[PDB]
Image (spheres, rainbow, N blue to C red):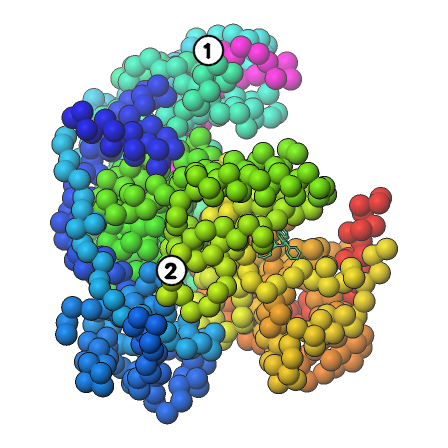
Amino acid sequence: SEESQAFQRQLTALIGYDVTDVSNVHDDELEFTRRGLVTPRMAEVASRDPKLYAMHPWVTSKPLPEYLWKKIANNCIFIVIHRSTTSQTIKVSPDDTPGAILQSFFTKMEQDFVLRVCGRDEYLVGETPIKNFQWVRHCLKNGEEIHVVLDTPPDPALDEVRKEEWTVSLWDCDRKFRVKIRGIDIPVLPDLTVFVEANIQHGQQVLCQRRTSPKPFTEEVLWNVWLEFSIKIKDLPKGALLNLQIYCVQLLYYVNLLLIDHRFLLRRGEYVLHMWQISFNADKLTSATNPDKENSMSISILLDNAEMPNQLRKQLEAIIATDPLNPLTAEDKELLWHFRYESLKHPKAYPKLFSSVKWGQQEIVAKTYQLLARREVWDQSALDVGLTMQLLDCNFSDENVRAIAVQKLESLEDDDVLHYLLQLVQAVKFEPYHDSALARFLLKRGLRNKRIGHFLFWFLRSEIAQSRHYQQRFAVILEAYLRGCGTAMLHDFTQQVQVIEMLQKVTLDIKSLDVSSQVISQLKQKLENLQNSQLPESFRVPYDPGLKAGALAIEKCKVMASKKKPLWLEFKCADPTALSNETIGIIFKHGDDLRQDMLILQILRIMESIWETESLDLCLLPYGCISTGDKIGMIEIVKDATTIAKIQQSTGAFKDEVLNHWLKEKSPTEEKFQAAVERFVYSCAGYCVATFVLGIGDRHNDNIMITETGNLFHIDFGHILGERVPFVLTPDFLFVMGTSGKKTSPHFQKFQDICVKAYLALRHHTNLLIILFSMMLMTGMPQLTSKEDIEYIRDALTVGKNEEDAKKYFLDQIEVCRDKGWTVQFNWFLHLVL
Ligand SMILES: C[C@@H](c1oc(=O)c2ccccc2c1-c1ccccc1)n1nc(-c2cc(O)cc(F)c2)c2c(N)ncnc21
């Protein structure tokens, strides 16, 4: 009880927000959730395997791609086992496991040791086939030797968890719901007339709307009006958001209040809600009141209480085939609902079905629940992630509807959970209530696997550190996680948090003071002062928790000559068993919002996985990136890489030959050089298709880079998000491919061919990409997120069009880029002057 004060204070340090704080609330939902999440934590902690949790092996049940089979020699796998600076090689089959492989070593010169990967904290352990380990595939994909160091396993005791110590409406009537608007109050006015618009909302649909009369916008406006709504109290659905907004027209302020609380009670009493200052985005839905009580506006209220016909089946099937953004007419909705039992047979009909429910009626919602009660077809259906994701977006409130979504995610293996985790963390923003099946899914999955747990922490910490709209909720979830992750990890997270808090301090202090002599001088002094006392011996790399970064390579650290002034920092590896002498690189940056970088890079990983399922590898580089705080964070330095603008600038006269010449120098042999040119054709093709689909194609060439081995890759997506070519394919790139102006070439034929395959590949997962894009814009990018902005990707994916018309579309977009040529790239420098 005296010791728990320090532990709670330790948890507040890791979260960067006090969950015991009660200044910004009008109920106990957050405290109820803190208590509510105890059971799921303690359940999952009680059921987890200690040794497997300790070693967390990164394995899969998905097949090896048709591309990766060619790198197997003679059904053989060369593992290089190390032990005390003395190595040995072993012949291994693809279906072998570590236990069989260890017994082979002991024969050639028992069950105490474990086979750990060289460089990383990663363990080839368990009863998984050696073909289906992620690390075995990294070494096959990159073309590397599978190196592993024999040593003792990590002791489970280190991962000990601390001991802990702790339907319908009530007041139900056929009365019409009403709220008295007493008045509003702000200390300073920021536009002479104003009025309150009150809205009964369920899942971003206005069930009923009433307004006050207009009045002069003075510092204290008092209407004292009862607004009677049409909707009856018994007809209020759970999760019904009372949304209050101030207009002048122009929406200036907004706040929300849940009409039915976490204990199923109707909301009643005097409330003084502090509002947010200002098209739909996730912030607009929040149950959170404004914490800035001094400067913010406040509203004050009072609550006192047979077989189907042929044509129609075909008509219904037509509705079910359409894209997620395809509008349902009131005719369509009436059809879907009337034949809801037929609609229930088709899992793909579900989003549209539950979008056809009149959530303003108790009889209907009752019927909808009776319908969901018999879901044999839903449970037996093969997991569709895109379908599951629809049902967790802003259009669906209602626990049961969202619950069957989460029910399908349960089947995802750990590998697939990481792929979708960020989006799923963001989807918590669309939850009406703090405690939710989704929140509990995340917590559970985080506690079961350290890798998922690691990235959960940081994704949660990102939003806690900068979203006032949702910091309160996410913190109660992260506190819940950290209370079961283990003492080993809590110490590990603390190390990382303390390293980051140092390194951001140097970044911002140097940002205050193009490059000069004193800036180069002061940095090398600043990094020495931290390394000599403050900074640890070693710490986990947040963007990659296999790597333990050691000391600073102070020689290699430097500041960019840019307005934003990022810190390029470089670390030696703390692991002595690491194969090379190569450094772990990091870019700390203030000024950009790196949550936009996060979300784009995460879709690129999803695009790779899609491409893997249809045996394609377009050679993307989705480097590590983690947002740590407000306009601040961290990026993985991609090694042996330059910007294509530096290659050129060595005014604004761009040159066709130079990139091709640049590859000839950094690659010694021709067969390497051609291998670079090959890698360029894929990488360039993949980044063209991906950026077209995401609407972020038109980049200026400072924000496009290439590796010495010809791997093209884009950067700085946060910069862009906030005459026009569809994607960067400047002449310099085409010159590597052996074509100039009108001409064609054998690599350029291969470019168009892959681009077409990839594009059509992504189009086989249209719905998934539509929702990822939809949810990105709503949760990630406040700047632009209207109906038309979401509907960009429809036109990009050529929805409702066959593979021939679609092929023609993308090839024409390639022809545009050439027809304009250097035009746009030159126009950036021209715009700096103009
Ligand atoms: C532009 C370049 C760069 O960025 C610095 O910060 C920097 C700092 C001190 C000196 C040179 C630099 C350079 C640099 C410029 C020209 C040639 C070589 C290096 N850059 N930028 C990102 C990068 C990517 C993001 O998504 C977000 C972000 F904020 C930065 C990046 C990366 N991930 N990997 C490798 N290089 C990278």
| Magenta-drawn stretch contains 187 | yes
**Whether residue 812 is visible:** no
**Label 2 crowding class (10 Å Cα cut-off): few <14, some 14-19, many 20+?**
some
Q: Position of residue 685 (x, y in %)?
A: 61, 71
Q: Where is residue 128 in the image (x, y as percent from the top left)?
A: 24, 73
Q: Mark 2: which amino acid?
A: Asp
Please report the residue visible at 47 percent of the width from the left and 43 percent of the height from the top.
Answer: 531
Quarter of the picture containing the N terminus is top left
Looking at the rendered structure, which numbered label has been put on residue 771? none
- Circle 1 is placed at which residue position? 183
Vertical relation: 709 (above or below) 691: below
Residue located beneath label 2 in the image: 575
Can residue 736 be seen here? The reply is yes
Q: Where is residue 278 in the image (x, y as percent from the top left)?
A: 55, 28
Residue 703 in the figure: left or right of residue 363: right
Q: Quadrant of the C terminus?
A: top right
Q: Which residue is drawn at 44% across and 86% down?
A: 70
